[PDB]
Image: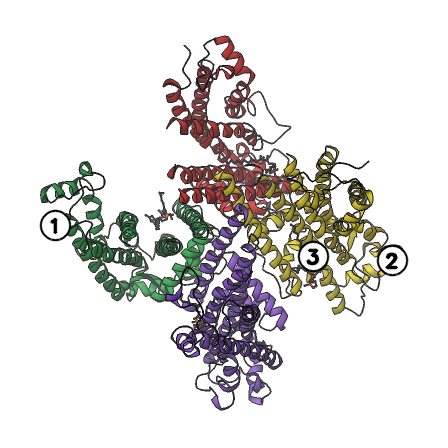
Chain colours: A yellow, B red, C green, D purple
Amino acid sequence: RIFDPRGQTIHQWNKIFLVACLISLFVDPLFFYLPIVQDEVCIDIGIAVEVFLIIIRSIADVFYVIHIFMRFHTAYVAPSSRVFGRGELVIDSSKIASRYLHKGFFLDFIAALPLPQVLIWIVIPNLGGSTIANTKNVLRFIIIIQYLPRLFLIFPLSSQIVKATTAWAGAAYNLILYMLASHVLGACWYLLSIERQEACWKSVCKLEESSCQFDFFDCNMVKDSLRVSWFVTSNVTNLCSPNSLFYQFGIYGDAVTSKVTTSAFFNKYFFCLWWGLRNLSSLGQGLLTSTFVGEIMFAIVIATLGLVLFALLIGNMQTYLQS
Amino acid sequence: RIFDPRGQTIHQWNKIFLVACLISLFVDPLFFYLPIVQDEVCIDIGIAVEVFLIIIRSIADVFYVIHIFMRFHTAYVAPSSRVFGRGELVIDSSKIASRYLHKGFFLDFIAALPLPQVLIWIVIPNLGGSTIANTKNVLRFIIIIQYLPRLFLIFPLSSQIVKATTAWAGAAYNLILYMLASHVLGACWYLLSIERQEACWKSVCKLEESSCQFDFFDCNMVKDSLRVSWFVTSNVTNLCSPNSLFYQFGIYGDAVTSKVTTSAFFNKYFFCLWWGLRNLSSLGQGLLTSTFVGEIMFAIVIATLGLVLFALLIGNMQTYLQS
Amino acid sequence: RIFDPRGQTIHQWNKIFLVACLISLFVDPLFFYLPIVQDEVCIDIGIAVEVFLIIIRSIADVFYVIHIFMRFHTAYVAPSSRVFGRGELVIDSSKIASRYLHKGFFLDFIAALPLPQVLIWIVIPNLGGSTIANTKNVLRFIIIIQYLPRLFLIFPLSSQIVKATTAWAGAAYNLILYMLASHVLGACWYLLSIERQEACWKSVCKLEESSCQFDFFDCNMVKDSLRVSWFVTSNVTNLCSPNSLFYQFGIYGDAVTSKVTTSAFFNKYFFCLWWGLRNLSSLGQGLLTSTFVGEIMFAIVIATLGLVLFALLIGNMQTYLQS
Amino acid sequence: RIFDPRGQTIHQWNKIFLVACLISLFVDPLFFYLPIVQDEVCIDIGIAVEVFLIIIRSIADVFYVIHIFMRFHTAYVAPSSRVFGRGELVIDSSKIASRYLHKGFFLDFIAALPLPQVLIWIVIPNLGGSTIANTKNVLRFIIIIQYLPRLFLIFPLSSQIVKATTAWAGAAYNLILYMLASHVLGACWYLLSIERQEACWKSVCKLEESSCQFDFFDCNMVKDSLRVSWFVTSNVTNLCSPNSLFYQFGIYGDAVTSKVTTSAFFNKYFFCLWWGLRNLSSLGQGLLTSTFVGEIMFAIVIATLGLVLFALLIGNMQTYLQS
């Protein structure tokens, strides 16, 4: 059942797979919005939203597995058989599999690994208790390690769609990509702000090591008598604010003053998407960072992305107007 | 009395209609500047300015009715008779009316409906008392529901004018588009800031529900003894300020600190026009919103409009310089 | 002694006239830096800098008069005698004078009028004592009335210089124009901030009509016994500051906090030039104006100039790299 | 042993020399990050990082000397022997040396001088004790005096590499130049902020001439009894802050508020790099300077560099899109 590379089944499958990849690209950064900072100073996770996102990601991974299957069952054109553009067809399944494994299979398999799901379920909780690591909100960012190759996969595939079927197709696509970059940067900023607030809490606990340890900032122990007794005699709610000059919050300060980390899922999502869009359009200006290397590099990445994306938008609109 | 589409009567009518549509597009957002926040914490409406705007709107409406009447009596080129461009003319009134009804009549009829003057006069006040809704200043935005179709009519019609009559007509036209977009965004910002201040007043009333009720911020009840007795012992004047953290004013806070909602019509109009133009040139930067989805979406729309308009301006200037 | 329009004497005269026009365009805005706000809350005029600028403007006006004389004594090509480019020359002095008077003489004569000199010397002081008007700092802006036609003369003449003698000639020329716009806008902003501070002083005087009148803010009367007695008991020092919420300084408030109205000529000049450059590059963003129509219109003009200039710069660099 | 100008040895040497020159351009501004402001209000020099930078710069200068020595022994195409491209080879060493001395030797020699390490070792300390000058942290900027000619050598030489080896070579090259400009501007801003804080300390000492001289702000005298006695009774810590309105810190105040001058080398380097990149992308907006001419000139230079770099980047991206 080898499908023709320039046939109809593969064209329809690629049309569906572009939508599936776009859905996966949209859903992956949403995993960064799960942590919630509560008024009692603790980080919880929205269970219902977590399960919903995991279900969507599982559907996307099923689609990716189907794509890998169809790529093991697709034909190719031999480079040496290209007779005036007529490269014929190859039906050898073994040759197709060898060609796929030599080039293309590795990156597609990496992109199809259910990394967020295993990280959420069978890595952090249950037997894989990372008490020694104590970086539950940091490991989520390794999704980016898988997100970056997957983002690459959107470039050639969509190009094939361009071959499948203009003036309006150069600016709308670039604005969609620009919104995607804004979405990813906003989710990254939200998770980094959560990490910054957790670091401020850890510094406060270090200042108050007499009656605190690095276990009081989890909402599963908020009702403990020790937790409330420490909370009523601590000024963590006032020290961990951008107004107080105790900890350098930097660009993450807007996540504490505006209570973004406490707001509902849609409020926080739209706030962070607008943050990313605004700091991508403004070329990273207004990102008055602290003296921390990671935040500075995040701001530099945002500025560079804004520069290249604005240049692409200007060029695309110039091309559209000239044609 | 069928008019020639390429003739002189229709050309002159289109020249008049371009100016009429430009005036109508300039006047429609001005209805958002009518509400006035007075020093007694209430929202009034300038009766004289409202009457003048309704008169101008009715003039635009009768011009649109004349345009519809004229288009009911215009000839069209038969697609099947296009013999090397010479498509002749169709004179049959019934055929012309049927063709116009099939394509074109609905969208032109929508743009000619006197929706704003109906809403102001015979929808909200008098028989149609919307006491339950209590959203008098929110219904105005449904003018946008009609504004967007009308904004469409400029693009073809002006192009037709281009056919009727370059290097200087590309940058100036896009600057006019920029002015119109900034004016509309400024009017929308003014009305949304009025809504935000009214929402803060409603929150204060809820906090003081013992002596306040949800009909109490109307200027027709200012002289009431109950209202003054409540006001002399109420802290609504400082709770609904961006300085206080009682309510998240966000980007609308600049309309409370600067007191544009209480200024004269020209001052408020120019302030809001400059606000829209500045946040369109800054690509939405400086729009530090709150965690409210509507305000965030407004900021995102402003940033996207700034992106597309600046890209169009750069492309038009590049075309001008290359020509 | 009619000179050849395609000859060498007129070529050299145009080369030196471009320099003279550039110097005159650089010098006219400097007259806006003359008023100085002193620590005694008064506005004085720097006599030495004023005299130097008047001398430079006199030299420029002499050059302009020589230019208009030479234009009265230059030949022209008859439009009806253009036989395949060989349009011959016209030597009749009467015909040349009539042609110049019909078109060209009016605006050239307008630019050659010593308006700033007569305004400074024989309009405001001496016989023309503007005691009733009391707007000495406002009249200077009618230099702009002469400045706008003069700025016109740069555009054709420079093009003629192009005909006298590339890839590098597009970016540098546009940067020179951009610097000129920044210089003019900075001088205008300095004078407007002077006017705003004087208006705040007048408002304070109105608040203190018992012991103040509209002369007390003139530095010639600073040593008056009434002046010192009012000053030792007046709070105009802190009331007219952007920190206090007494007067809406707006975008001009930055000139009071930084004390640029008091500093030396070089400091204030460079601060205002950088202000114009920054608010021209930032597309007018950060110009958070008050509810005053004049300030808002000035900010709108600055933003539109920034838009057109940045688009022109982008287009010029695109042309330079492409060619 | 004259090398062929279009041979293989010179090609490889130029490939090495481009990397060497890039290293030298990256290392020279790092000398500006050496001064450190300590909590005892004094400026020290990191000896270890200074020695490492001196060693790297010495290696780069040895590479420059090797380049000069070898290009003394290369043939050149005779201007009069260019017979249809075949310009032959000049083997005469005397003629090659004469041509090099006439054109090429001066700029290559001035760019190979060990001026930075000479200043660090045998100019400022030891015999050349600049007690009278008292500009230990100011002289470093004369590295820029040699840096600009060395910045020139990149533009031709890199072009040769282009001749030795596209669509991706326009955006990447522009971004490399842009990052280099950001790095240089950040180093210059750090050293200028150090200078501003030192000037504030000098002003404070002038305010405290009774018990202070211009030596208490050197970290070699921090442990002196007079030093500690003055420090315990001096308020230099409060007066020399951006919050206190004592000294106009201007755009350098962000360096004191963020305590970047005290941070470690990596923190300060990345903070200053992000500062330069942000103020270069923002076209100098947000550089609210003081009334000081040097700071204003620095801001104007930053704005002009941002303008030209953004224009070049837009043009390069347009070229990439169209080709």
Q: Dots 3 and 2: beta carbons under 8 Å?
A: no
Q: Main secondary structure of the magenta part?
A: loop
Q: Is residue D270 left or right of residue B274?
A: right
**Residue with the most extreme bottom position:** D127
Residue D77 visible to the viewer: yes
For disc 3, the neighbor class at 10 Å (few under 14, some 14 to 19, many from 20) is many
Seen at 41% across and 14% down, the residue is: B3
Badge 3 marks a residue whose secondary structure is helix
Distance between mark 1 and mark 3 Cα atoms:
77 Å
- Residue at image mark 1: C2
Distance between mark 2 and mark 1 Cα atoms:
98 Å
Callout in the foreground (2, 1):
1
Span highlighted in magenta in the image:
D208-214
Q: Is residue B294 left or right of residue C141?
A: right
- Residue at image mark 2: A128
Provide residue C63's location: percent of width, then percent of height: 19, 57
Q: Look at the image and say whether residue D209 sits in the magenta stretch.
A: yes
Residue D53 found in image quarter? bottom right
Question: Which label is found at residue A192?
Answer: 3
- Comparing C122 with B126, the one in front is C122
Badge 2 marks a residue whose secondary structure is loop
Q: Look at the image and say whether residue B110 sits in the magenta stretch.
A: no
Residue C122 visible to the viewer: no
